[PDB]
Image (tube, helix red, strand yellow):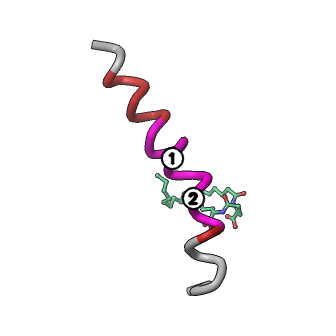
Amino acid sequence: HAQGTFTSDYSKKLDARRAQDFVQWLMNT
Ligand SMILES: *C(=O)CC[C@H](NC(=O)CC[C@H](NC(=O)CCCCCCCCCCCCCCC)C(=O)O)C(=O)O
């Protein structure tokens, strides 16, 4: 889907939604 808006418009989320919640615990121990 959105083969034209599924990549570019997908580089400003995981790297903050899959990194924040993550790196949020990784550094909590
Ligand atoms: C996020 O779900 C994908 C959104 C992304 N594009 C944008 O961030 C901007 C367009 C808009 N996005 C938003 O406003 C935020 C949407 C959040 C919805 C989250 C629901 C859960 C889905 C999780 C999917 C896995 C993604 C990795 C997260 C660990 C929009 O939604 O269109 C895009 O590429 O669509």
Residue at mark 1 to residue at mark 2: CA–CA distance: 7 Å
Q: Secondary structure at mark 2?
A: loop
- The amino acid beneath tag 2 is Ser
- Image-quarter location of ligand 1: bottom right
- Seen at 36% across and 23% down, the residue is 25
- The amino acid beneath tag 1 is Asp
**Circle 2 residue:** 11
Asked whether, in this view, residue 25 is left or right of residue 2, the answer is left
Q: Secondary structure at mark 1?
A: helix
- Seen at 57% across and 58% down, the residue is 11
Asked whether, in this view, residue 23 is left or right of residue 8, the answer is left
**CB contact under 8 Å: marks 1 and 2:** yes
Q: Position of residue 1 (x, y in %)?
A: 56, 86
Depicted 20 relative to depicted 13: above or below: above
Q: Residue 6: which quarter of the image?
A: bottom right
Q: Position of residue 13 (x, y in %)?
A: 58, 52
Check the picture and name the quadrant holding the C terminus: top left
Q: Position of residue 8 (x, y in %)?
A: 62, 69
Q: Position of residue 4 (x, y in %)?
A: 64, 84
Residue 5 is labelled as none
Q: Residue 10: which quarter of the image?
A: bottom right
**Circle 1 residue:** 15
Asked whether, in this view, residue 6 is left or right of residue 22, the answer is right
Residues in magenta, as a range: 9-19
Depicted 22 relative to depicted 17: above or below: above
Depicted 26 relative to depicted 4: above or below: above
User: Which residue of the protein is positioned furthest toward the left in this rendering?
Assistant: 29
